Image 1 (cartoon, rainbow, N blue to C red):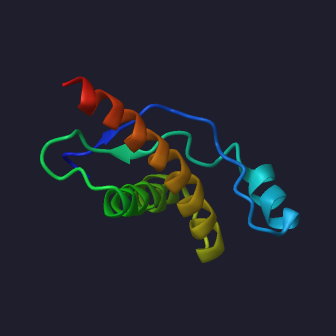
Image 2 (image 1 turned 45 degrees about the horizontal axis):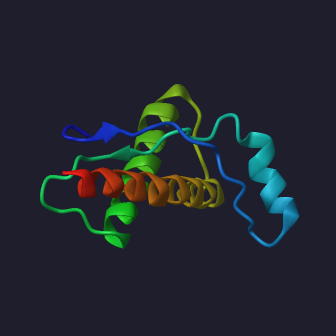
Length: 104
């Protein structure tokens, strides 16, 4: 990283994968899942969808480095389940920061 920050910690979402097996599969592991998303302040860039797509990729990467360095390596399906959780939180943090963009 460098230049990034970490936003407010929020509720680890129950994504519905449409199989309650998968919902609960993440849900058992959800203690280890990320609790907050890495983000950046409102410089110039903002964007909706592509900024989330970056915030996702960063937070998953920083899992896949900083947590995987700990001998805790993910698999593709676990990464995708994280991507969803991180996306869900990040949609929210963006929307929240956009309320203070209006306050400027």
